[PDB]
Amino acid sequence: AAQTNAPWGLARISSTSPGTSTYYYDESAGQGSCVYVIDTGIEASHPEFEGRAQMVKTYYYSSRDGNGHGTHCAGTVGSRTYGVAKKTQLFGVKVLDDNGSGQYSTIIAGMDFVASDKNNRNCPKGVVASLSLGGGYSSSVNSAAARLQSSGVMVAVAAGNNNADARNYSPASEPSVCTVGASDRYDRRSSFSNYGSVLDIFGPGTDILSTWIGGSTRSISGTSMATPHVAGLAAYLMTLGKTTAASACRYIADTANKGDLSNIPFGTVNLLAYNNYQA
Image 1: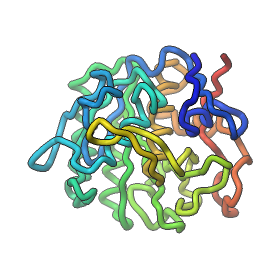
Image 2: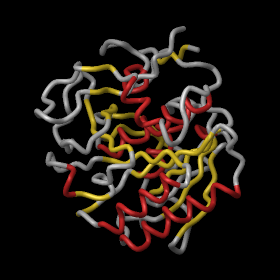
Image 3: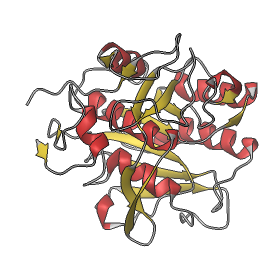
């Protein structure tokens, strides 16, 4: 399948070169997979989600996304126009308040929630969780991410936006999950992207168009935006049967575009997420 005039990041993940604008992908499109977006919520009524999104849990007075960040990330996972995996099922877990903040205890509870809640959902092709969040190093936060991964969920986490080594941030620094840095449309490391040996992969993160609250759209930047590209890619590849939740991060690294990014610090992987789709 071909989506013309796609957001640059979608075109990038199906291309061996920057500078194109059509996204190519297998029409299975993540059907039968599920992606949890653990964030500020999801505006599931947005036409872009086509009834495939739903809120399943909140720790606050509403499950609605009063911020936009979670809706944007969910759109990059799975919206019809802005998403990588256009037929996946999206489940929102609101661990962040409408200012985008959340206590680590709530975030940990949300991860353990997903590890159990997947047993209440129909995801025959597999389960992914996208975590566009983080703070300073916490062994308890890392352990929660490790449990979620161990339970059979492909966990993708943001590296962070400090232009610093991600070893000092959580859940970015957890080795067993997929830690995602950000790149721009010219294949440069995004100016804010964290780096370091704990990163597994880069995805598009600068000037990413996606869904927003109020039935709208906007372009924003962050490792928060790169993470759902990888989460959606994992769901797509799992639906194709090419990999599993336990092996998808490694498979994405195996099959990535290699050595094509600029300003990658010595010791950080130079790997850009790529779907290897041959039309």
